Image (cartoon, rainbow, N blue to C red; front, side):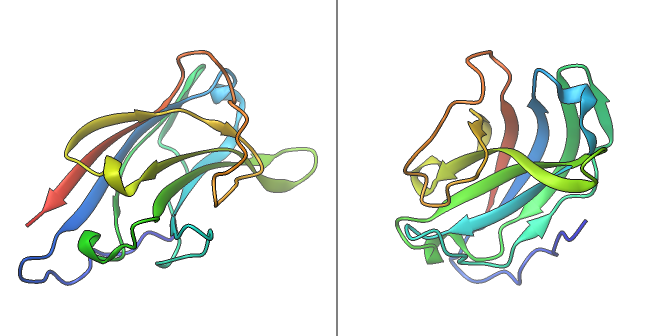
Amino acid sequence: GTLLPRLPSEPGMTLLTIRIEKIGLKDAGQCIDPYITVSVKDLNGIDLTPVQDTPVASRKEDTYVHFNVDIELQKHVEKLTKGAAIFFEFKHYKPKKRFTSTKCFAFMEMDEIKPGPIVIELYKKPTDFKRKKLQLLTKKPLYLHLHQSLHK
């Protein structure tokens, strides 16, 4: 885990916290030491904030990996450029090849930042930070489950 503390609050500014609940994957339970990397890129796909990594998942299940962890957005909402997008990359350890690979990614755009649950689809690695070319990981209803919290 490389998760950061909530940023210092500001008058009239909003902070966003994103509880990552779970992610569906037809081979969910088979992934070893799985976690997620959360970043925020501009339209050009460049980091607008420091990248964070969630600790390895609490519970796996045949078709679901449970996290139930909170992510603090490292920049106030009304300070993110219009083209920003928040990326979630599912990473796991490949037993034989002995390394960590990014299996898929899900992303949400500025205009999708609102309180309440939100389910995002999953796209095939390699992650496209400009999100211009996408291959759906599975038409199956196995998604990424998040809940968003907007402060002040």
